Amino acid sequence: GGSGQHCQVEHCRQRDFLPFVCDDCSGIFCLEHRSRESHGCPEV
Ligand SMILES: [Zn+2]
Ligand SMILES: [Zn+2]
Image (cartoon, rainbow, N blue to C red):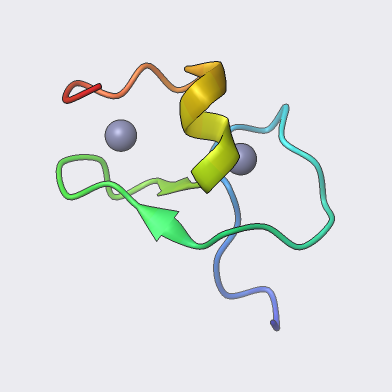
C-alpha cells in the first residue's frame, strides 16, 4: 500500500502480496509463501 508491510523473505517479489503475519513471527508472510516453506514457520 505505502511501504508499510513487506514480506520478511527478501527472496520474495516486490509485487503486491498477501499481508499475512505470523502470531509467533512478527515478520510479514504471504499466503503462497507458506506452501514454499521458505520462512520455516514454527507452527507449519
Ligand atoms: Zn513472501
Ligand atoms: Zn512464521
